[PDB]
Length: 108
Ligand SMILES: N[C@@H](CCC(=O)N[C@@H](CS)C(=O)NCC(=O)O)C(=O)O
Image (cartoon, rainbow, N blue to C red; front, side):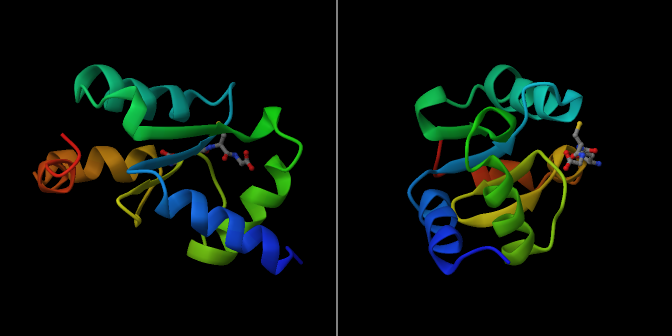
């Protein structure tokens, strides 16, 4: 299983960044989520930590830690202000119900 140190590291990165996005360079859904955040929602790049797990030594451990934490297995795995949003579909869902704006206010 994933070490407790890895779990702690991931929890820390999520808490230290207004928006946290576990991603993979070749993931169509990650491109979509980031496009929405940066271009459509105009979120400042400095407010988002984007980790391309497929390009990181600990990428695999981080993805397993995330499953341990929130039960999600896929990327993108998005958090906004420490609150787990989910994947791209989850992000788009919140926009359609008009609930994403209230979450981004403190960040924008
Ligand atoms: N419905 C999900 C789909 C995400 C998805 O399928 N991501 C792929 C990468 S393109 C994935 O995580 N596959 C399993 C893995 O990479 O471990 C979303 O909208 O985020």
